[PDB]
Structures are given as C-alpha cells and as structure tokens.
C-alpha cells in the first residue's frame, strides 16, 4: 500500500519534501528511524508523481 520514497534524511530535508509534495496534492508521511534519519512514504498510486516533483524541485537539498 505505502511505498518507500526517500530515506536517510535530515529533519529539515524531510519537511521540505513533504511541503513540496503537499503543494502538488500528494500526501506524504515522514517516518523517524532514529539514527538512520527520516524516510518519506507515499501511497503506491502517488509514487510516479512524487518522484516527478522530487526531480523537478531537485529534492532533497
């Protein structure tokens, strides 16, 4: 159901990714994996689109 979009992220990096996805009507989850940083999840359907916006905005910074 929920596929794993990015991982190994800073907290601010994570937030910006979620912001940019939210701005394009994709809802994402931020997941704290402690020493491994945050990861970003979306819903399978939104994967292609989410990858598009992350390329487009050149995320993560």
Image (cartoon, rainbow, N blue to C red):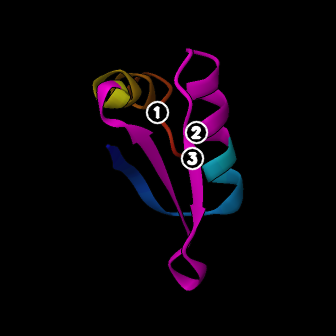
Q: Which residue is drawn at 28% across and 25% down?
A: 48
Residue wearing tag 3: 29
Residue wearing tag 2: 17
Answer with mark 2 or mark 1, whichever residue precedes in sequence: 2
- Asked if residue 61 lies left or right of residue 43, the reply is right
Answer with mark 3 or mark 1, whichever residue precedes in sequence: 3
Tell me where residue 53 appears, x and y as whole percent.
44, 23
Query: Spatial distance from mark 3 to mark 1, Cα to Cα?
Result: 19 Å
Front: mark 3 or 2: 3
Residue wearing tag 1: 58
Residue 25 picture quarter: top right
Residue 42 picture quarter: top left
Residue 31 is labelled as none
Front: mark 3 or 1: 3
Q: In which quarter of the image is the N terminus?
A: top left
Tell me where residue 14 appears, x and y as whole percent.
61, 51
Judged from this view, the residue extending furthest toward the front is 1
Front: mark 2 or 1: 2
The crowd level at tag 3 (other Cα within 10 Å; few <14, some 14-19, many 20+) is some
Tell me where residue 33 appears, x and y as whole percent.
54, 75
Q: Residue at x 44, y 31 (%)?
A: 54
Q: Which residue is drawn at 56% across and 27% down?
A: 21
Residue 44 drawn above or below residue 49: below
Residue 37 drawn above or below residue 53: below
The residues colored magenta run 16-45
Q: Which residue is drawn at 49% across and 50% down?
A: 40
Residue 41 drawn above or below residue 21: below
Query: Spatial distance from mark 2 to mark 1, Cα to Cα?
Result: 10 Å
Answer with mark 3 or mark 2, whichever residue precedes in sequence: 2
Pick the front one: 52 or 58: 52
Query: Spatial distance from mark 3 to mark 2, Cα to Cα?
Result: 10 Å
Query: For numbered disc 1, what is the local secondary structure?
Result: loop
């Amino acid at each position: 159901k929920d596929k794993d979009l990015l991982k190994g992220l800073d907290q601010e990096q994570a937030n910006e990714v979620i912001a940019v996805l939210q701005m394009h009507n994709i809802e994402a989850n931020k997941i704290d994996s402690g020493k491994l940083g945050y990861s970003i999840t979306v819903a399978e359907p939104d994967f292609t689109a989410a990858v598009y916006w992350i390329k487009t905005y050149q995320l993560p910074p």
